[PDB]
Amino acid sequence: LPMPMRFRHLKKTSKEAVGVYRSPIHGRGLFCKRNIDAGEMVIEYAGIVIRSILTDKREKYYDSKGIGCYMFRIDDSEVVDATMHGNAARFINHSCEPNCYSRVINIDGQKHIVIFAMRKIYRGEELTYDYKKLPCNCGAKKCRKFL
Ligand SMILES: Nc1ncnc2c1ncn2[C@@H]1O[C@H](CN(CC[C@H](N)C(=O)O)CC2CN(Cc3ccc(Cl)cc3)C2)[C@@H](O)[C@H]1O
Ligand SMILES: [Zn+2]
Image (tube, rainbow, N blue to C red; front, side, top):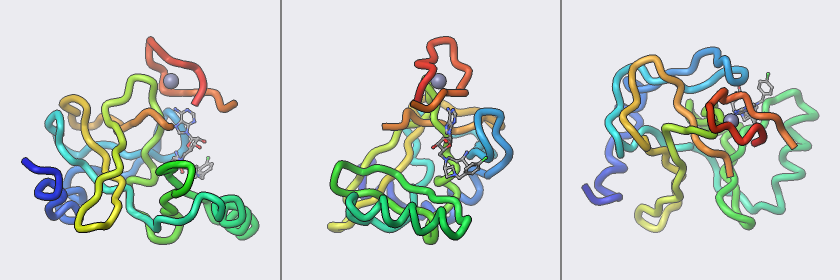
């Protein structure tokens, strides 16, 4: 199905497909509630597309208020800030053998970060993607040992 046609009713369908629980990788993570087919559009990484140069001061502000800072790097110029206007996708942890991957899609001139399943994902599994200094806890055989 075409990419804009696939961005269909993600809000309703992701609410039934994924949930947030404690993760053995780190803190809380995103896990699936039902089997997700390979190639399936899982969830949008919801948030505000902001200028990359603004992230330092935004993270400094959040940190000074004891508010967890949730951001996803688009490119060297833009970042999605999911801190205030985010959804469950902000809890997706890194893995060196991920079952998901992140892509920047464009629908009706608007940029959205969407998470896709790389393989069939089975009920109970944690959803992970390769993030674009910090030790890694994915626990995979082929672990890069750093994020
Ligand atoms: N494979 C991994 N191995 C080790 N650590 C990993 C791995 N994948 C992700 N992480 C950590 O999660 C951070 C990204 N966050 C994902 C969701 C996080 N698990 C959370 O519970 O908030 C959102 C960040 C904002 N949130 C604030 C926060 C800080 C500390 C704690 Cl305990 C809970 C929340 C963290 C990333 O920067 C790493 O620090
Ligand atoms: Zn790893």
